[PDB]
Image (cartoon, rainbow, N blue to C red):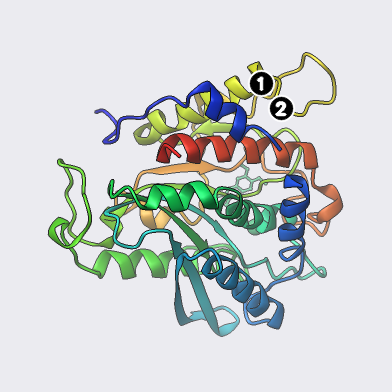
Amino acid sequence: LKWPRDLRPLAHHDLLYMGQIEDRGDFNATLRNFLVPRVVGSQKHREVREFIVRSLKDLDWDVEEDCFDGQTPHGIKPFCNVIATLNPSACHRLVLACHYDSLLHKEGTFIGATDSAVPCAQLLYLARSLNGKLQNQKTRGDGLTLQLVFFDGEEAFERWSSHDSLYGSRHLAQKWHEDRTSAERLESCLERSEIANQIDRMEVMVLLDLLGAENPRFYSYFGETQPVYRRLVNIESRLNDAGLMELPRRRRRTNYFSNSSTVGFIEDDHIPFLKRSVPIVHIIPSPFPDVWHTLDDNEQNLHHPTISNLNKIFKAFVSEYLQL
Ligand SMILES: COc1ccc(NC(=S)NCCCn2ccnc2)cc1OC
Ligand SMILES: [Zn+2]
């Protein structure tokens, strides 16, 4: 079955503009705010939450918090998902997502630079760097918008289990599934749309996780979103053709988005949405970074040229999907 939205290839001019990176400076300033331990229940976690909210409210986005208390192996804990929507009334959302909590590591202070400080900064960076074009797109009345979700409580408090993980994403998926709505209440839904609740408005969720290490390897995890995944492959290829990727030597190419699918199961914030038929693109590397869940998942183990390259792909992707 065809993707419900016709995916119009980015014009060369727009590819080149989106592939240009002061841009490094703004991104790094944003990232600095996330490179702090931010365990659920902590003051720094609160400060990170508030920084996300303020940053997006300053860009004139609608920002909502889904706050609740949940039982954990460490007792009751407070959680707050942050949901920012460019145009609340638009029927359909391109959803980009990540988690903003950091793992409570028993061995010491854990920064979670890839997991997921970088993805958090990347979402804010997209909103900031594309603001002018996004605000223009919002005026079109075309029924499509951008939505950013920063999930809380992705990490387990003890041993990962169905009950001890994904606290924020499980909560939000249930909340949205139970919140009934219909096309007549929303702006410009696609003709063939079946809208019965808020989750139906998530046209695709692109979940970023464990980004920032050198040479990530992505694969298509879901046949349902192959048409969308293939746009990432294509965009990356075109950025390389144009010489816009940062490589250690001339005449190398990035090959992050493999033109293949993998049979691998990864549990993450997409799971509660996947179970409710939300199409998922899971932008998570396989293998995971070497530093995964170690005290070495820190700022210095990030690979800045890779981050810049990913930012180009992501900007071009959002530009292509929203026709910015
Ligand atoms: C070390 O390499 C792996 C370890 C575990 C798994 N399997 C699962 S189900 N992981 C769930 C990860 C949830 N998460 C996301 C961010 N922080 C935690 C796969 C891995 O390599 C493909
Ligand atoms: Zn983790």
Q: Earlier in the sequence, mark 2 or mark 1?
A: 1
Between 10 and 45, which is closer to the camera in this rendering? 10
What amino acid type should be assigned to the residue bearing mark 1?
Answer: Asn
Neighbour tally class for label 2: few under 14, some 14-19, many 20 plus, Cα within 10 Å: many
Residue drawn at 71 percent across, 77 percent down: 44
Q: Does any atom of ligand 1 lie closer than 8 Å to the CB of label 2? A: no
Question: Is residue 166 toward the left or the right of residue 128 in the image?
Answer: left
Count of numbered marks: 2
Q: Is mark 1 within 8 Å of ligand 1?
A: no
Residue 223 place in picture, x, y as percent: 38, 31
**Residue at 71% across / 27% down in the picture?**
245
Q: Is label 1 in a helix, a strand or a loop?
A: helix
Q: Position of residue 295 (x, y in %)?
A: 82, 59
- Furthest-top residue in this view: 251
Quadrant in which residue 5 is drawn = top left
Give the distance between the C-alpha atoms of the residues marked 2 and 1, in whole angstroms: 6 Å
Quadrant assignment for the C terminus: top left
Q: Are marks 2 and 1 in contact (CB under 8 Å)?
A: yes
In this view, the residue farthest toward the left is 184
> Which residue lies under the disc numbered 1?
240
